[PDB]
Length: 53
DNA sequence: TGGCATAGATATCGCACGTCTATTATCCTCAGCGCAATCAGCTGTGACTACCT
Image 1 (cartoon, rainbow, N blue to C red):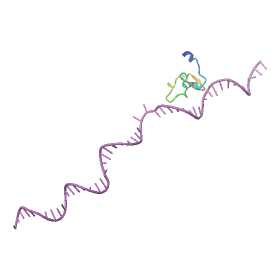
Image 2: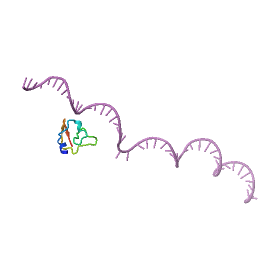
Image 3: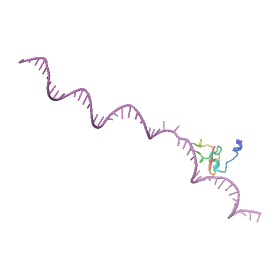
Image 4: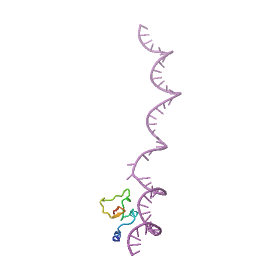
């Protein structure tokens, strides 16, 4: 099931990345949330925005 | 027959509305210091009495 889920390239809507464990966009990060490491792998690009786990 | 203007279906991000929890100061009340008019003991005054000449 995890392998099948990873087969999805990226959702079509930026809003789908909000508070999503597999999506986790940049703008949606809360006050206490930060990307570590800052050199993490990019899962994809949605409308110019990089996707991180 | 072939390329592109234009009408249809579908979301989509930005903007505003309803709601909550934070991680270290403020406010009544009592025992101990004061200020203002009587009253008793210290001090001053008058009289009793032993002592010296």
